[PDB]
Length: 81
RNA sequence: GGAGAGGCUCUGGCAGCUUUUCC
Picture 1: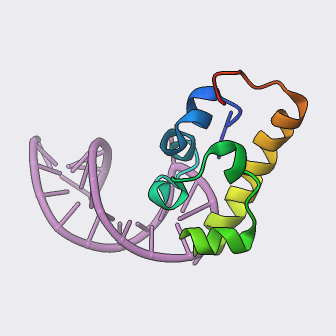
Picture 2: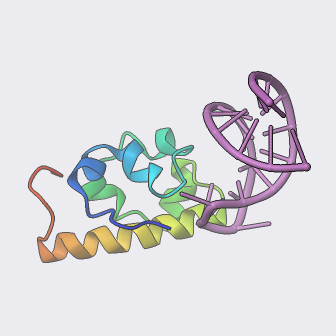
């Protein structure tokens, strides 16, 4: 259960974005990809990243749709980029 | 019997299992 995700310190630091999601075991599978683009991932992209669990991957797509939303609204800080 | 700290595993939770630590 996340509470923010739209946070520039988490968005710049993918491990700590994923800490707030209990997915920080897959932090190396989701690293090498910046937040701005990670969010645009697909279910197929996630299983090719290393996100083989169904629960995991579905919860990335959720987490992702939220941040994207705030990106498309511009409510995010310039320090996330 | 209870709590803390790692490792692992999805069904992704103050989840489960496991290894340790303290009582």
